[PDB]
Image 1: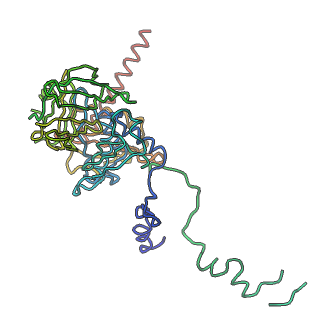
Image 2 (image 1 turned 180 degrees about the vertical axis):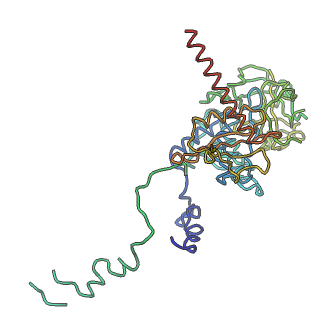
Image 3 (image 1 turned 120 degrees about the horizontal axis):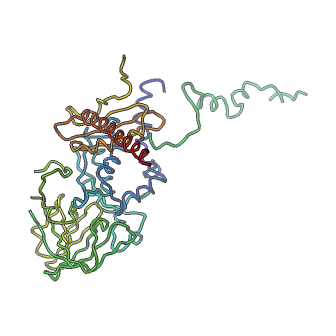
Length: 147
Length: 46
Length: 134
Length: 103
């Protein structure tokens, strides 16, 4: 489009971000499709642990303050889930850190109790890994699926 | 509405209704300037 | 300061299709009604069946801005125990009369302590350190 | 003599007011220097946060973020990282020459 009125329209009305939900049923038509879904089930798994070097790399790898991805002008990082013997970060903590740097600082963290496509039986005895739990913008239970 | 000549030449009614019509092919829809076409390729880095 | 301290006897160590984590089922040696269900990184701190673990819940280590990697001459409460985890309390459940069960999460690594007297000390705090000995 | 100004660039849109946090952008570089440089910068006891990110494969860019604690700027942490990587390579080159003779 060759004028500012047509620009404003393509940036605020017909733009992609304003088309997350279809008007047919009010359901989402935007999301990740294949590798990302399989990657998430592995990354958010209990068995997935990360060192300070690994953890910080995964953060800056997807969040770049120079590209305006941050909301705090400094990459904030959570303390490790394992202090002694070796300092280690869980996979779920990367998901907590990504939200902590992309959601506004003025607003409180997200609170959601959702479910997974993968049943608890697959993750062994007494696991609650089907229950997706977000308390004050922190992934505390459950893996992340296509769901 | 004219007699058969030994496909006839189209009239002005035929010009407005050639296929879909002048209204559908050149008013409701139009070929545009400042536009491009290409095969799409996937990209997770954008 | 400390919020909870007890010595537990391990009854189960289940991997559950995990190569590094294990679900520990324990019972207190002092209190009869007390029970424990905790996920630990068995790769770093291995736990075997019929073992004595000194599980301790603390608020901090004897106002902090952020976590820093260890640097020469630093003293902590963690220096007394072998395996230390940092997590949050997300659920407070009551089981029949007098008995109360707390739910903790150390980044997916869940813990469920069942007791009665700890209702005052154990509170839903976004900061709770879990320290284990032996 | 003229020094090249297009290689290393300080992204002022991300630099801390003063002076610890900054994002640097290097042209004609990728994982090769990137992962090696962030590894060496992370060994610094003053570096709080460090990582590397390639914006896109088609564009010849390399981004490296250095967030430090006090008494050291991100520029100093980068300069130390480059100075240490050079010395690290000298160690590799020295040990390899010695073992060639040792054969």
